[PDB]
Image: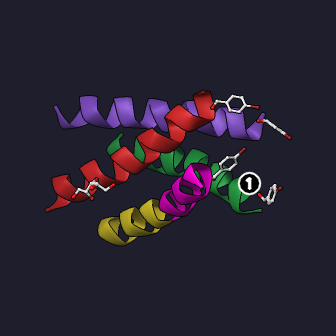
Chain colours: A red, B purple, C yellow, D green
Amino acid sequence: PLVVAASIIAILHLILWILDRL
Amino acid sequence: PLVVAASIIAILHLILWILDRL
Amino acid sequence: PLVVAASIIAILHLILWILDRL
Amino acid sequence: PLVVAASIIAILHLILWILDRL
Ligand SMILES: OC[C@@H](O)[C@H](O)[C@@H](O)CO
Ligand SMILES: *C(=O)c1ccc(Br)cc1
Ligand SMILES: *C(=O)c1ccc(Br)cc1
Ligand SMILES: *C(=O)c1ccc(Br)cc1
Ligand SMILES: *C(=O)c1ccc(Br)cc1
């Protein structure tokens, strides 16, 4: 569950960071 | 342990980054 | 596949962030 | 190696980001 959660969070983080930079 | 550590770190990184942006 | 996707994304995210900072 | 590398990179990314902010 930890690795699954982190994987999802890593994807979320990239998306959010892109939106922040835009 | 590397993968467990990186997973924890990914989650922490997102939390810190959100807090930084706010 | 989720872990593979997240692994690719983690590498991409670092590259993008370094280029943004530079 | 993909997962090992991504794990290393996730740790490096947080270290760099914390240092960048500080
Ligand atoms: O998994 C892809 C999802 O549809 C969203 O995260 C979009 O990419 C957001 O634009
Ligand atoms: C949750 O992501 C998880 C925990 C242990 C093992 Br093994 C696989 C996945
Ligand atoms: C530490 O996260 C770790 C190392 C080797 C294997 Br296999 C699983 C997890
Ligand atoms: C996809 O990355 C993936 C899914 C299940 C298991 Br077990 C390993 C990898
Ligand atoms: C590299 O990280 C790697 C590739 C295949 C398997 Br199985 C474990 C680790």
In this image, C19 relative to D11: left or right? left
Give how far across and how far down residue B17 sits, in percent. 32, 37
Please state the quadrant of the image where ligand 5 appears: bottom right
Magenta stretch contains residue B2: no
Give how far across and how far down residue B12 sits, in percent. 46, 30
Q: Quadrant of residue A9?
A: top left
Q: Which residues are magenta?
A: C1-11
Q: Is residue A16 visible?
A: yes
Q: Is mark 1 within 8 Å of ligand 5?
A: yes
Q: Is residue A17 above or below residue B8?
A: below
Toward the viewer: B15 or D12? B15
Toward the viewer: A7 or D21? A7
Give how far across and how far down residue C11 sits, in percent. 53, 63
State how many labels appear. 1
Toward the viewer: D8 or A8? A8
Query: Which residue appears at 61% of the width and 35% of the height?
Result: A3
Give how far across and how far down residue C7 sits, in percent. 58, 56
**Dot 1 corresponds to which residue?**
D4
Toward the viewer: D22 or A2? A2
In this image, B10 relative to A3: left or right? left
Magenta stretch contains residue C5: yes
In this image, B12 relative to A20: left or right? right
Q: Quadrant of residue A19?
A: bottom left
Residue type pointed to by label 1: Val
In this image, A12 relative to C5: left or right? left
